[PDB]
Image: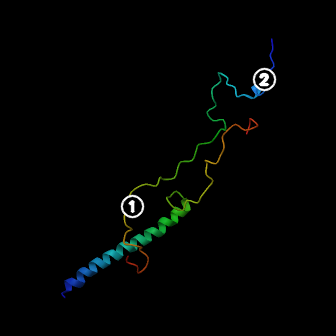
Amino acid sequence: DGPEKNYEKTMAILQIEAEKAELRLKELEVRRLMRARGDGPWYQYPTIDKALIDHSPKTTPDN
Amino acid sequence: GWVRPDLGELSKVTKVKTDRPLPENPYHSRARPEPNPEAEGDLKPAKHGSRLFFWTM
C-alpha cells in the first residue's frame, strides 16, 4: 500500500502513546502528592467512625 | 401537709424551666475540620485502557 498507510498509522500510534506517556507521568506525581497531603479521593486511611459515640446522659455530670 | 411519694415516683424524669441559655459549646469544642473534597462526577471508560506497559486495552 502507499506511504499514507504507514504515515497516518504512525500518526495515530505516536499520538496515542504520547497521551499515555504524559498520563503516566501525571499519575506518578498525582499519587505522590495525594499520599503526602491526603486531601484526595483515595489514600484516605480509615479512622474511627463518629456514629459509635454515645451522647446520652451518663452517671457523672461532668465528662 | 407532706405525702410520702409512692414507689418509683422519685425516679421519674422531670422537666424544669431554667432561664439560663443552653451552652452552645458545652465541651468547648474547637473548629470542626473541613471535609475532604467530595467524591462525585460521572464515570467514563479509562483513558487508553490500563495504560500499563504494552497493554493497549
Residue A12: name its quadrant.
bottom left
Res. B2 image quadrant: top right
Residue at left offset 76%, top offset 37%: A60
Question: From the viewer's perspective, is A40 left or right of A56?
Answer: left
Residue at the spot of label 2: B6
Does residue A24 sit above or below B33 in this rendering? below
Q: Which residue is drawn at 26% across and 81% down?
A: A9
The image quadrant of residue A8 is bottom left
Label 2 packing within 10 angstroms: few (<14), some (14-19), many (20+): few
C-alpha span from label 1 to label 2: 67 Å
Residue under disc 1 on the same chain as residue under disc 2: yes
Task: Locate the N terminus of chain A and report the quarter of the image it occupies.
Answer: bottom left
Q: How many labels does the image show?
A: 2
Quadrant containing the C terminus of chain A is: top right
B29 to B14, vertically: above or below: below
Pick the residue in front: A32 or B37.
B37
Image position of A8 (left or right of A29) = left
**Residue at coordinates 61% horizontally, 33% vertically from top-left?**
B24
The chain letter under disc 1 is B
**In the rendered structure, which amino acid carries the disc numbered 2?**
Asp
**Secondary structure category for the residue under label 2:** loop
> Where residue B43 appears, x then y in whole percent?
39, 61
Q: Where is residue A52 in the image (x, y as percent from the top left)?
A: 64, 48
Of labels 1 and 2, earlier in sequence is 2
Visual colour scheme: rainbow
Tell me residue A31's x, y (percent). Answer: 50, 66
Q: Name the residue under label 1.
A: B43
Report the front residue among B49 and B6: B6
Q: Which chain carries label 2?
A: B
